[PDB]
RNA sequence: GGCAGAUCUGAGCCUGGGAGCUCUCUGCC
């Protein structure tokens, strides 16, 4: 899974 | 025991730009 944080996408798990 | 939302990060930090450390509020079966 995917999250937007502070100018960018990060991935955490799927 | 399992899937997913918040968002100008809802938010601390780094042995950072990493399927990283972390941290809060909630749903569904």
Image (cartoon, grey):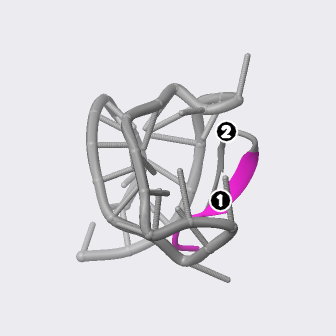
Query: In front: B18, or B4?
Result: B18
Q: Which residue is mark 1?
A: A10
Residue B15 picture location, percent across and down: 44, 69
Q: Is residue A7 left or right of residue A11?
A: right
Q: Which residues are magenta?
A: A8-14
A3 over A1 or under it: above or below: above
Query: How far is mark 2 from mark 1, CA to CA?
Result: 10 Å
Query: In which chain is the residue bearing label 1?
Result: A
Residue B28 picture location, percent across and down: 42, 50
Residue B6 picture location, percent across and down: 58, 31
Crowding at mark 2 (Cα within 10 Å: few <14, some 14-19, many 20+) = few
* Residue sitting at x 65%, y 59%: A10
* Residue sitting at x 74%, y 49%: A8
Quadrant in the picture for the C terminus of chain A: bottom right
Label 2: which secondary element: loop
B4 over B6 or under it: above or below: below
Crowding at mark 1 (Cα within 10 Å: few <14, some 14-19, many 20+) = few
Quadrant in the picture for the N terminus of chain A: bottom right
Quadrant of the image occupied by residue A12:
bottom right
Label 1: which secondary element: strand
């Amino acid at each position: 899974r995917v999250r937007t944080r502070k100018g960018r996408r990060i991935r955490i798990x799927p």
